[PDB]
Amino acid sequence: IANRFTSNIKGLTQAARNANDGISVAQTTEGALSEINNNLQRIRELTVQ
Amino acid sequence: IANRFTSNIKGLTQAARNANDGISVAQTTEGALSEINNNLQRIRELTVQ
């Protein structure tokens, strides 16, 4: 049972690290999307003009 | 909703600027029309004479 618990603890810690990496991926993609959105807003203003 | 509000505000402001340009155009044309009308009135006076 101690072996099983050690395996589970190590796996869960590594999974937490993986989830942190995924959060980083999401943040980077969202920043790129925000810049694209600002460009689109400016283009719409130019079209209205 | 904030993005939509920003787009609407920008569009309305630019449309107001274009409308102001419209008043400018109309004022210029009305000034030319006033000059033409004054010339026509003087021509009428000369014809009456």
Image (cartoon, coloured by chain):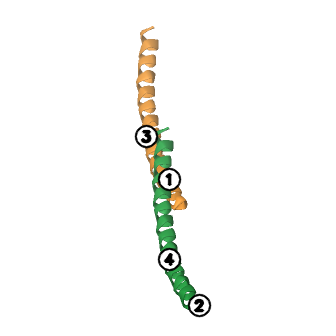
Chain colours: A orange, B green
The residue positioned farthest toward the front in the image shown: B49
Q: x%, y% of residue A42? A: 47, 56
Q: Residue at x 46, y 40 (%)?
A: B2
Instruction: Provide the chain ID for the residue under circle 3.
Output: A
Q: Which residue is mark 2?
A: B47
Residue to which mark 4 is pinned: B34
The amino acid marked with disc number 1 is: Gly
> For this rendering, which residue is in front, B25 or A23?
B25
Residue positioned 56% across, 84% down in the render: B40
* Residue B5, x across and y down, in percent: 48, 43
Label 1 sits on a secondary structure element that is helix
Q: Could you give the CA–CA distance between mark 2 and mark 3, rounded to whole angstroms?
A: 82 Å
Q: Pointers 4 and 3 in contact (CB under 8 A)?
A: no
Query: On residue B36, which mark appears?
Result: none
| Chain hosting mark 4 | B
The answer for which chain carries disc 2 is B
- Horizontal side of residue A3 vs B45, given as left or right: left
Quote the CA–CA distance across marks 4 and 1: 34 Å
Graded by Cα atoms within 10 Å as few (under 14), some (14 to 19) or many (20 or more), the crowding at tag 2 reads few
SS assignment at label 3? helix
Mark 2 or 4, closer to the camera: 2
